[PDB]
Amino acid sequence: SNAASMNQLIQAQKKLLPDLLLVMQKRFEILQYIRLTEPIGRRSLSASLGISERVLRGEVQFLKEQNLVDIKTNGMTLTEEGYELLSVLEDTMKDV
Amino acid sequence: SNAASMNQLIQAQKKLLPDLLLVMQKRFEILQYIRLTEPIGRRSLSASLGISERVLRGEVQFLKEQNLVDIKTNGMTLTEEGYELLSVLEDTMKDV
DNA sequence: GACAAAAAACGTCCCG
DNA sequence: CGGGACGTTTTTTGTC
Ligand SMILES: [Ca+2]
C-alpha cells in the first residue's frame, strides 16, 4: 500500500536509487560549508571537503542550475532559495 | 511518520535531487510497462517506450540486480518485490 | 553474447 | 577566482 511514513518512502526509493542518501548527504554538506565560508571558490571548497576539484565543480554547477548557489567572480554564495532549502534539510536530515 | 514530514522530505528532494528523481521516474515507468505487458522482451519493450534497445538493456539489468524483474527465455516479468514497489511509490510518483 | 565506437567522467593546466 | 580546454580513463551506446 501507499507509503505511510518517511522510513517507508526512503526504503522504497533506495530500491530505484541505491545511493540516494549518499548524494543527499554530499549535497547537504556542500550547502552547509558554503553557508559557513561564502564567498568560497572551487579549489578551497574541494580541499576543505576532501572531494576532487572536478567532482565538486560538477556538483556546484548543478546546484547553480537549481538556483541554490550563485557563482560569481569572487566565488560562490547561497541564494535565497539555498538558505531556505538548507534550513528545511537541517530538520529533515535528522529523521533520514 | 507524519504526512507533513513526508511532504517536507519530498519537496526538499524535488529541489536538491531532481536529476536523481528523473532516473527514478524512468525506471518506475519501465516497471509499469512490464506490469501491463509481461512477459515482454527488450526489443518489444524498447519500441513500446521511446528508447533504444541498448539503453533499455542497461536499465533492465539494473532492475534485475535489485530483484525487481525476472528475465526468462520468454522475456521479463516483475518479482514480488517489483509489484510491492509499484504499490508503495504509486502516489508520490504522480506528485513529482 | 561479441566487437566497435562514442560519450562521459575526470585530473590538471590555461588565461585574464 | 571562474570559464575554457586538453589529454586520459571509464562507462555507455550502437549494431547484429
Ligand atoms: Ca512474500
Image (cartoon, coloured by chain):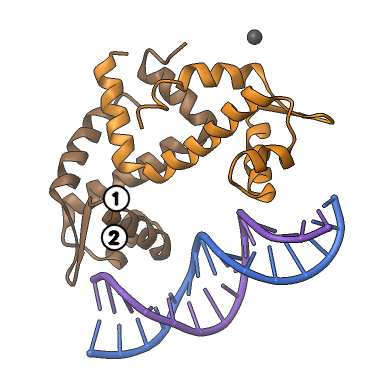
Chain colours: A brown, B orange, C blue, D purple
How far across and how far down the image is residue B5, in percent? 26, 21
Where residue A75 sits, quadrant-wise, is: bottom left
Q: Position of residue A18 (x, y in %)?
A: 52, 35
Figure disc tally: 2
Mark 1 lies on a secondary structure that is: helix
Q: Position of residue A91 (x, y in %)?
A: 22, 28
Q: Amino acid at mark 1?
A: Ile
For the point 68% across and 27% down, the residue is B69
Tell me whether circle 1 and circle 2 mark residues in contact (CB < 8 Å): yes
- Label 2 environment density (alpha carbons within 10 Å; few <14, some 14–19, many ≥20): many
Mark 2: amino acid? Leu
Q: Residue at x 64, y 28 (%)?
A: B34
Q: Is residue A8 visible?
A: yes
Q: Nearer the viewer, residue A68 or A24?
A: A68
Q: Residues within 10 Å of mark 1 (few under 14, many from 20)?
A: some
Check disc 1 and report the residue beneath it.
A30
Residue A93 in view of the camera:
no
Identify the mark at residue A45; answer none if there is no mark: 2
- The answer for how far apart the CA atoms under marks 1 and 2 are is 8 Å
